[PDB]
Amino acid sequence: MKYGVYFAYWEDSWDVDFEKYVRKVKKLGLDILEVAALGLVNLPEQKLERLKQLAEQHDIILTAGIGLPKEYDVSSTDKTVRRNGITFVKKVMDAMHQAGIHRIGGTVYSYWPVDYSGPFDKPAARKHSIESVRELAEYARQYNITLLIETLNRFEQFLLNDAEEAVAYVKEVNKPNVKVMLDTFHMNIEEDHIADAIRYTGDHLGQLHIGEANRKVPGKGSMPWTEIGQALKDIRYDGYVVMEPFVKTGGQVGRDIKLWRDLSGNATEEQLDRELAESLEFVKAAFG
C-alpha cells in the first residue's frame, strides 16, 4: 500500500504552488502528494514540467483532486453546461499529462458542492453523468489516466452517497480506467458499517481517502482504524491511501469544507508536519 496527503492540509485556498509539498511529503516518509486539479489546469507548461521533475527527483507519486463547479456540471440537463464541463476536464487531463499525473479523483462526474436551494432530477443527472464519464474515460486513455468516482455524504452530493450506489454506477460506466474512491469522512455518515462498505467495494476500490469523523488526522478521533485495516487486508488492497485532514477555518478551503471553528489549536506548518508524521505511524500500525 502507498500512503499520501492532500496539500490542502496546510493551505487556505485550492490554487497555490505545489513544489514545496513534494519535498515536504518525501521528508515525512509519504509516497504520494495529492494536488488540486484547479491549480494545474492553467499552470504554465514550465511549472507543470518542474512539478513532474521534482516528483521524479524525490520519487513521489502525484495524484489530482477535483470538485467541478456548477459551470462545469458534466451531469447537467443543460447541454451547454455539460459540454463546457467535459472540455474543462479534458483541459485538466492535458495539464495532468505534462505534470506526469495519472489519477484524478473527487466530484469529476457532477458538480460540488451541490446547491439544494434549487430543484434537481437524480435519474436524469445520473444518465448524463455516466455518458460524460464514459467520454472522459475514453479521452483519458491516451494519457493512461484513471478517474476515481468519489462516494460523498448527502449534504455535498445526491448521486452516489454510499458504496452500493458508487459500485452500481461504476459497473454501468463499464470502463477499466474508472474506479470507486471511498472516504472515511463520507462512509462515516452514510454506511451501516465502514469496514463492510470497503469489503463490498473490493476490486472496484481505486483509492481510499482517510481522516477522522470531523476530518482531523487519523488517531485524533474514534474511526475504527483496526477494522478498516482488516477490511483492506480482506480485499488484498495494494492501492493508494491518501490522508485528507482539514483543521483550518477562515479560507476558501475552510468555506468549501464548511469548517466554522479551528480544529488545529492554531497549529503552525511545523506542528501540522509533526502531527501528520505521528498520524502516519499510527495508521501503518493500525493497518499492519
Image (tube, rainbow, N blue to C red):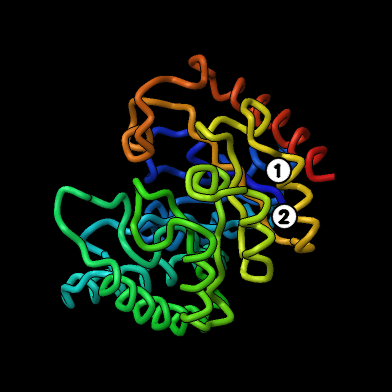
Q: Which residue occupies the foreground of this view, 284 or 124?
A: 124
Q: Is residue 11 left or right of residue 128?
A: right
Work out which quarter of the rendered image holds the C terminus and state it: top right
As shown in the figure, which amino acid type bears the numbered disc 2?
Asp
Residue 95 occupies which quadrant of the picture? bottom left
Q: CA distance from mark 1 to mark 2?
A: 8 Å
Residue 106 visible within the image? yes
Residue at mark 1:
26
Which residue ends up furthest to the right in the rendered image? Answer: 288
Q: Residue at x 36, y 63 (%)?
A: 159
Residue at mark 2:
59
Q: What percent of the width, then of the height, locates residue 242?
A: 62, 48
Work out which quarter of the rendered image holds the N terminus and state it: bottom right
Q: What percent of the width, then of the height, locates residue 196?
A: 66, 55
Q: Which residue occupies the foreground of this view, 78 or 251?
A: 78
Q: What percent of the width, then of the height, locates residue 166?
A: 49, 66
